[PDB]
Every structure is written in structure tokens, then in C-alpha cells.
Length: 30
Image (cartoon, rainbow, N blue to C red; front, side, top):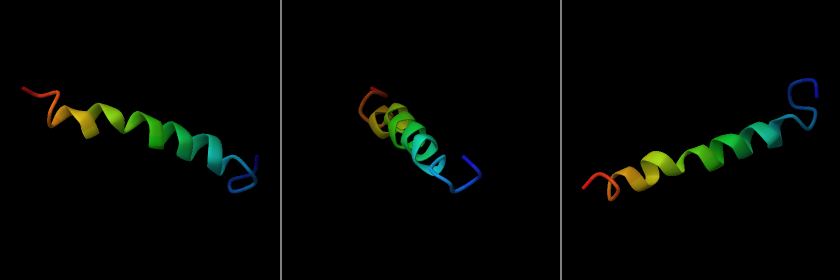
């Protein structure tokens, strides 16, 4: 922890994961 100090990963992962919702929306919209 200490903004860079590992923390980066865990967060980026949350982001990288979350994205799906919209990534798929464009199909999972009809």
C-alpha cells in the first residue's frame, strides 16, 4: 500500500473486471 506500492494491482483488477457490464451492453442491449 502507499499509492503505487502494490495497491495499483488490486484496483486495476477491480476496473479490468467491472468493465464487462458495458463491454457486453452493446449486445446485451437488445
